[PDB]
Image (tube, rainbow, N blue to C red; front, side, top):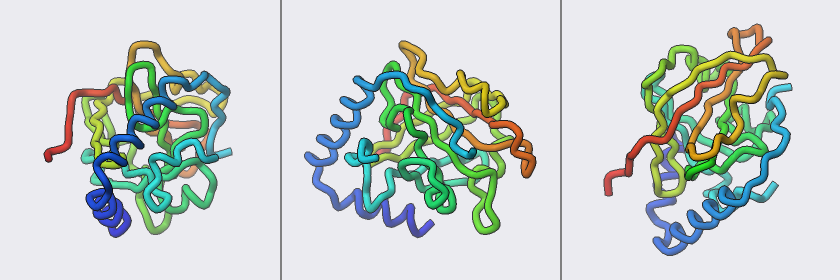
Length: 190
């Protein structure tokens, strides 16, 4: 809402060369990221090039009428206000051999957040708005796993993936719902 408008307003006032340089720095990070143990979020400075007044963009999910601001990390402060980029995952700038993981609560009293993520189906398309770029991902896999069974958020060579992660069943939170999309061609209108 206000936060998303503010983000896009700020970006539109930024220097084209700086936007380009920031983007390449994110790509460099994604090109050199080593596999690491990725923990369940519910129970740094490395993304600084993406930060615009602490936000790194937003995730747009037309299937559930959501546009949710994104931040770095999964602390409770972050998750009370938007979605968080998971520690150890790729930055949300795409590229071959990348897998970004974006997490949000299955609803809060005053924001639906990922409450309706269970409504998403294979073929649905969601969009990551990062700096002045918009990256489209099409849902190709939906699984629910125990917090201990987290292999599906790992980097797969040759692919460009983005997973939306929340808790499930609603209010029972015994498991995690992972909605995986694969990059499809899309560029924001100029």
